[PDB]
Length: 434
Length: 100
Ligand SMILES: *[C@@H]1O[C@H](CO)[C@@H](O)[C@H](O)[C@H]1NC(C)=O
Ligand SMILES: *[C@@H]1O[C@H](CO)[C@@H](O)[C@H](O)[C@H]1NC(C)=O
Ligand SMILES: *[C@@H]1O[C@H](CO)[C@@H](O)[C@H](O)[C@H]1NC(C)=O
Image (cartoon, rainbow over the protein chains, first blue to last red):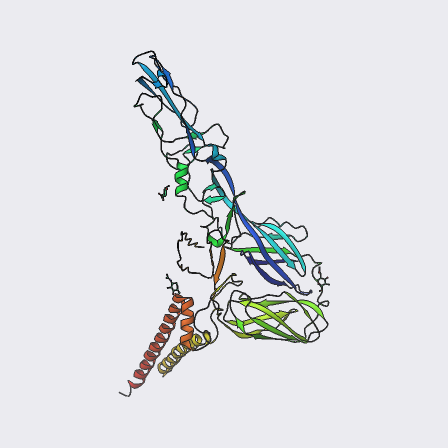
């Protein structure tokens, strides 16, 4: 038997329904989202870290011209200075008076500690939601994982559940994502080969051990002022360090719908944002015939101290005079009130107590025991506790959040105004007919 | 949908107020685990009682909705009274115009 329903995306908060075939006893269907994740498809643009500036040993040629060629090194900057007179410990360094030339080199590479402190730039595509479902049908429990895409069946051969497309697409990650040490940021890094000095991604490579490193740090070589053999140079600050200084807060703290960002792979787990259509092909072995289940001769429902809140606030008692002892499901036929218990054991005569959670100020709903309705009818009070540590199990909706003796006043005033309209109209017609 | 995230370094002994809605709010304090809280409809009134208690209870929960409902019912009774008065006045002058 195939049953289609719609569950909330909130992790935890089990969803209850009952399945009623024409010739079979109803059974409880119990759909719980125990876990979820929203993993986008990522491709790595580059890696980056704080660069290490390598200044090689200077070249000195004693009154003979020097020039330097192009190099494949990362941000290779070169300059030649003529008319030098270098000195080291020991004395002068060339045999020639004032035509001596010095060639100064400079480039960058990865720091030795980039194996730990480094950032990875990613472009992420549309994310797919995969949920872990606990399905209790009758009294059989199955745990599975399914993709929320509309056509892929769940990971269960004996149940064949299909999760329909998600109500809305959330995708907490922006198009460009930076990951550093498990911290995830929505940063718009520059493209590969488009380095900017003093900003993030000033040095880039395909991997940490890659040899094709490219960088555009603002390095420049100065003419040596004193006559030692140092290489004077000025460079822009490390754009990786500059980004670390003002990275802001990661997406683990700034992400809607209260779901936590995890790496390896990049994903957002336990997001509560939409509604998932779920279709279950319940096997016929789970069903039982209507004659097998105990029957209800009469049943009455009395609600005692209904308190509308997020937890299971409110209790009701079903008094029944059933036939033969047996277990049968119970349900609340309302979208504004959900029971706590699913199946109960009934005897020849007695009363059973159930706990329910509602978002409406009145307990005005139909409770079915063994498939037999009971139409519970009472009032509920606003809660005393302002703040609770669990989410609401029932969505709040109009026409139920407004109670009677508040609907009564509105209907009375509207009916009075309409009564004045009708009496004015009929007196006008009576005057016109004369 | 709107994660109004705040981050602040606290020194000394202070107090911080945070508005919590039905969707909930989490706070992390130092190295502690995140703590999640949710707000209930605990408005200081009475949905089943005299009308002023109902109005203040539903005004603390959803202000603008109840204000426009009150404006709508006031407009409805005003238009109904005015139209009924106009109709009965027209009928009265139509019945008394031959006698005059
Ligand atoms: C389900 O309940 C029925 C009646 O209570 C019982 O006979 C049966 O063994 C139960 N099934 C399982 C799998 O526990
Ligand atoms: C940058 O770093 C300096 C010292 O490292 C610090 O004082 C400053 O607050 C940081 N942030 C900005 C935005 O300048
Ligand atoms: C925080 O809220 C309480 C109760 O609403 C109030 O008494 C207090 O003044 C508020 N504190 C601040 C700093 O606004």
